[PDB]
Length: 91
Image 1 (cartoon, rainbow, N blue to C red):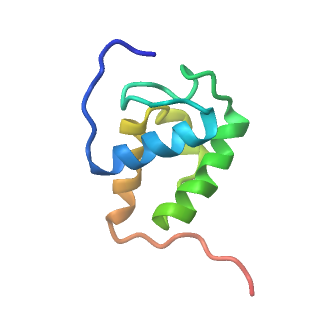
Image 2 (image 1 turned 90 degrees about the vertical axis):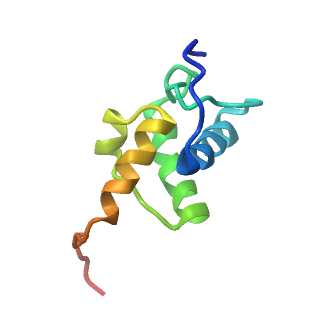
């Protein structure tokens, strides 16, 4: 429940919705940290999966620690728009 009450950018609104779905709230501001809503790191790991189902994008929990608000996660997502090879795995 931060007082900045900042407005939402395009990805940040999807993240606010995704935060609310897990937290059980009416709304999340782009300045509300996942932890300020009472969320825990374990729930933040599950958030990654829901973001992937809805938007098709993944974020490691490493970056999420530095990106506790929707506005933080959205810019962290945007960094992946650069040409970068994600690490592979076997088949």
